[PDB]
């Protein structure tokens, strides 16, 4: 990416607890051992555009 | 918000299907109304905070 | 013109699936409804019931109940349910006192001999027995407590017979003035008034969908369909969703698992002891991108 | 029955009850979560009465459920008695294990002044049995090394018994470890219980504590087993954890 | 100028119906009343519903 | 806010202890739920305004 060194530090310091911006159906159905929070939100009509 | 789905809001249970499998409309609808108003209240609160 | 996060109406379930434990035993309804002897009210009988299918159609064929009041479970939904535990509290009382067998009521029966939780869930069933239990000259085999120093607790059975000190006179636990025998009997005669006729009563107490079910209604099970959103019913717990295989180390006493939201996440199939996760049918938002109407209808 | 004369006893010992007295409030499976529940629990770091066998057991009151615990190596401690008068005038719950079958009764009992079983014989713990209404019997079977911690409570007609049996290597006092008690039995008895006593078969000791109505936070791990808990109203730190719904406070 | 025990009626009487509005009966022992009026009469049996 | 503690919200009384001393759980809980939702509504309104 075209992020700067400082920008890389910033993105690596703050943590974005959303499992990124991709979480497929199969990703949740395979993550049956942890009960991911984002999957629980997603199954109840709560989505993050 | 998701934890508020665990709330009974004075109902016998927080699960819709339990009420519907146990209770029938004339008095089931009251518990369903209680759950609906509680959850809609939680949503309204969340949207207001947002 | 623009994009709209439209509501989710696209998919609707088509069929139903019914799954229940694989028990063919018929429940002993007869031994409690068709009994030579009922327990007296002070010493009311409590029968565990288990390994049962509950049809309650034999009672239809033969019996005729005066009262059938169910708290927490309206009766028409009773066929498609399974119960964790079932206790039949059987006894006989006087006819009017049938009103007193209910939560929130008071009386000699409610206070001194028998008591229900205010949160009772289950069914009270009562029918007259004036032509079976009663006899000419009176029936003194059915007794009840008339005085107690205090009030009862739910499902508490006080079979004590010691003298009650009605007054301040300590009569050493022997009969005397101002202190009498707590137990009293009814005089049941076939010609006696309706309010004085004996009534057989049975109270089915249970608690629903919180533990493994061994007794259940008479509905027959079906085959299971995976990876399809279906209307399912497991041990009386109904719902709609897609059932998929899962790995969960359920304890022997644990029947249901729940997620953060306290919705049922997975079910242990009663027939084949495997765990299936449930996922909603209409997963996944759908957004419509469109030019504004008055120009085109393509989207 | 016989009467005891020779006693090598002491005043009742006292110890601290801590990180123990927690049981599963229900039979639901939940994992990797923190659940708050209000019920009768053993307050953490409370005072618990410590008793020894002489080198007999008194009758104690049954206040709103009792926590019992004891450490064992030869199965000396073989049952309990519960009731109000315990002299056959009223029904009395009896639990016994005579090395063959665990027996549960609610018969009206004339209890012996001094229970004792067996050295290797002489079952002598009661002298009457009338107007009984319950009986349960299991199948045949045959430092301190095994800790057994039980909770006995009586709620709306049900006598509820929770238990946990573990191996140990410790003799001096109760361990500092954490262990949750699973529900084992729920008997519909309908008995008014106010006083109770234990049963020995004649190194031995036990601990008795009393439950109080408290709110507790319970931690289910990835396998759904209780690994830790927080008392509420124990102290300001625990109250902060209790109101914040978390075991970590910034 | 009364203490209300309603235990004499227990000892002797036997009521067909005891319906309390606004006060469920089990909480009736631990209450005191400002005024009390007993409206007494006799009617036909079915009309007890009325 | 404190004046809103005087509101019945459709209940028989605004006092919790009166309801509990007069009524018992199976139908007392309904009035208690009514009071709770009314007062929680008042609190939510106050917090929103704040
Ligand atoms: C008195 C009531 C009593 C209860 C409630 C009880 C519960 C109980 N004890 C068990 C194991 C056991 N229980 C005991 C002994 C005892 N455990 C006790 O609570 C007591 C008082 C003794 C005797 C002093 C032993 C030796 C085992 C097997 C442990 C092993 O595998 O070595 C088990 C598991 C059964 C199994 O898997 O084999 C249960 C359910 N046992 C009893 O005797
Ligand atoms: C259970 O038993 C206890 C002990 O007898 C009862 O409590 C006692 O009741 C008598 C009679 O009213 C009183 O004189 C005592 O002061 C009471 N003692 C205590 C510690 O409360 C109790 O009432 C019984 N339970 C029921 C439901 O009757
Ligand atoms: C019950 O269980 C057995 C064995 O698990 C299985 O073969 C059977 O199909 C199940 N259902 C019935 C109705 O027996
Ligand atoms: C009960 O008895 C009656 C007559 O004695 C009989 O017709 C009926 O079938 C019996 N009930 C059952 C469940 O068999
Ligand atoms: C107890 O048993 C005796 C006979 O042993 C009997 O006379 C008495 O009526 C019984 N009491 C109760 C309450 O059953
Ligand atoms: C809508 O249609 C009318 C007539 O078809 C036209 O006059 C108008 O300009 C249209 N509006 C837009 C935004 O295209
Ligand atoms: C002695 O035993 C008798 C019963 O045989 C009992 O009544 C009495 O209380 C006992 N006394 C003592 C001091 O143990
Ligand atoms: C019980 O222990 C506490 C401290 O844990 C102590 O303050 C108290 O005095 C003890 N009880 C007695 C009777 O000494
Ligand atoms: C004591 O053990 C014997 C042998 O197994 C058993 O038959 C008996 O039932 C036990 N004691 C009681 C009171 O049941
Ligand atoms: C939970 O169970 C898994 C599978 O048996 C095991 O690997 C893991 O160690 C268990 N958790 C703990 C804390 O032991």
Image (cartoon, coloured by chain):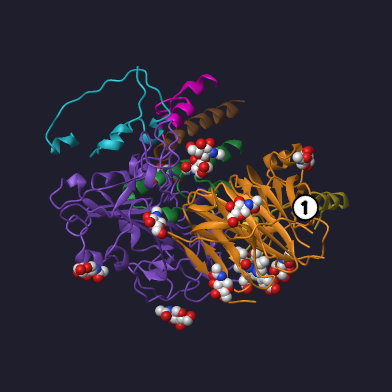
Chain colours: A yellow, B green, C purple, D orange, E cyan, F brown
User: Which residue is tagged 1?
Assistant: D9
Q: Is residue B22 above or below residue F19?
A: below
SS at circle 1: loop
- Position of the C terminus of chain B, as image quadrant, is top right
Percent position (x, y) of residue C272? 50, 76
Query: Is F21 one of the magenta-colored residues?
Result: yes
- In this orientation, does residue C205 appear? no
Magenta-drawn segment: F1-23
- In this orientation, does residue C43 appear? yes
Which residue sits at x=35%, y=26%? E4
Which residue sits at x=40%, y=70%? C18
Category of crowding for the residue at label 1, using alpha-carbon neighbours closer than 10 angstroms: few (below 14), some (14–19), many (at least 20): few
Query: Is F10 one of the magenta-colored residues?
Result: yes
Which residue sits at x=35%, y=40%? C105
| C205 sits to left or right of C129 | right
Percent position (x, y) of residue A5? 88, 52
Q: Is residue D46 above or below residue B18?
A: above
Q: Quadrant of ligand 4?
A: bottom left
Percent position (x, y) of residue A42? 58, 56
On what subunit does the disc labeled 1 rest? D
Instruction: Determine the image quadrant of residue C250.
Output: bottom right
Percent position (x, y) of residue C137? 16, 52
Q: Is residue A29 above or below residue E11?
A: below
Which residue sits at x=18%, y=33%? E50
Instruction: Determine the image quadrant of residue E36.
Output: top left
């Amino acid at each position: 990416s075209k992020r700067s060194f400082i920008e890389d530090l910033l993105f690596n310091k703050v943590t974005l607890a959303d499992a990124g911006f991709i979480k497929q159906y199969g990703d949740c159905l395979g993550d049956i051992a942890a009960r991911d929070l984002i999957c629980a939100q997603k199954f109840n009509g709560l989505t993050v555009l | 918000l998701v934890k508020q789905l665990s709330s009974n809001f004075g109902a016998i249970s927080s699960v819709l299907n339990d009420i519907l499998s146990r209770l029938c409309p004339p008095e089931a609808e009251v518990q369903i109304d209680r759950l609906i108003t509680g959850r809609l209240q939680s949503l309204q609160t969340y949207v207001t905070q947002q | 013109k623009g994009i709209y996060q439209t509501s989710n109406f696209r998919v609707q379930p088509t069929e139903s699936i019914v799954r229940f434990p694989n028990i063919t035993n018929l429940c002993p309804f007869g031994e409690v409804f068709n009994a030579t002897r009922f327990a007296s009210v002070y010493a009311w009988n409590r029968k565990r019931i288990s390994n049962c299918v509950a049809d309650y159609s034999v009672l239809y064929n033969s019996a005729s109940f005066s009262t059938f009041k169910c708290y927490g479970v309206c009766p028409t939904k009773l066929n498609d349910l399974c119960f964790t535990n079932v206790y039949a509290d059987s006894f006989v009382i006087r006819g009017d006192e049938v009103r007193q067998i209910a939560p929130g009521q008071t009386g000699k029966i409610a206070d001194y001999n028998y008591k229900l939780p205010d949160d009772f869930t289950g069914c009270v069933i009562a029918w007259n027995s004036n032509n079976l239990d009663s006899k000419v000259g009176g029936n003194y085999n059915y007794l009840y407590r008339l005085f107690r120093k205090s009030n009862l607790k739910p499902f508490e059975r006080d079979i004590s017979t010691e003298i009650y000190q009605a007054g301040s006179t300590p009569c050493n636990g022997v009969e005397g003035f101002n202190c009498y025998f707590p137990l009293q009997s009814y005089g049941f005669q076939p010609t006696n008034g309706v309010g004085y006729q004996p009534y057989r009563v049975v109270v089915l107490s249970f608690e629903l969908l919180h533990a493994p079910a061994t007794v259940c209604g008479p509905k027959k099970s079906t085959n299971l369909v995976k990876n399809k959103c279906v209307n399912f019913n497991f041990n009386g717990l109904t719902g709609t969703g897609v059932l998929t295989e899962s790995n969960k180390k359920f304890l022997p006493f644990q029947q249901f698992g729940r997620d953060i939201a306290d919705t049922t996440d997975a079910v242990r199939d009663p027939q084949t002891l495997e765990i299936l996760d449930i996922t909603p049918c209409s997963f996944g938002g759908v957004s419509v991108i469109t030019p504004g109407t008055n120009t085109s209808n393509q989207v | 029955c016989v009467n005891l004369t020779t006693r090598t006893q002491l005043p009742p010992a006292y110890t601290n009850s801590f990180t123990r007295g927690v049981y599963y409030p229900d039979k639901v499976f939940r994992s990797s979560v923190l659940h708050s529940t209000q019920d009768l629990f053993l307050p953490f770091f409370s005072n618990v009465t410590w008793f020894h066998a002489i080198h007999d057991n008194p009758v104690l009151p049954f206040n709103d459920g009792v926590y019992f615990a004891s450490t064992e190596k030869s199965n000396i401690i073989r049952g309990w008695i519960f009731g109000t008068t315990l002299d056959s005038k009223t029904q009395s719950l009896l639990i016994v294990n005579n090395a063959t079958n665990v027996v549960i009764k609610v018969c009206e009992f004339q209890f012996c002044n001094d229970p004792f079983l067996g050295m290797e014989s002489e079952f002598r713990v009661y002298s009457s049995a009338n107007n009984c209404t319950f009986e349960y019997v299991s199948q045949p079977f045959l430092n301190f090394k095994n800790l057994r911690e039980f909770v006995f409570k009586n709620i709306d007609g049900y006598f509820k018994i929770y238990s946990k049996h573990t191996p140990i290597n410790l003799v001096r006092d109760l361990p500092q470890g954490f262990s949750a008690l699973e529900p084992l039995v729920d008997l519909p008895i309908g008995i008014n219980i106010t006083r109770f006593q234990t049963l020995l078969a004649l190194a031995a000791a036990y601990y008795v504590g009393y439950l109080q109505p408290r709110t507790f936070l319970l931690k289910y791990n990835e396998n759904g087993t209780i690994t830790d808990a927080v008392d509420c109203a124990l102290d300001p730190l625990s109250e902060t954890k209790c109101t914040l719904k978390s075991f970590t406070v910034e």
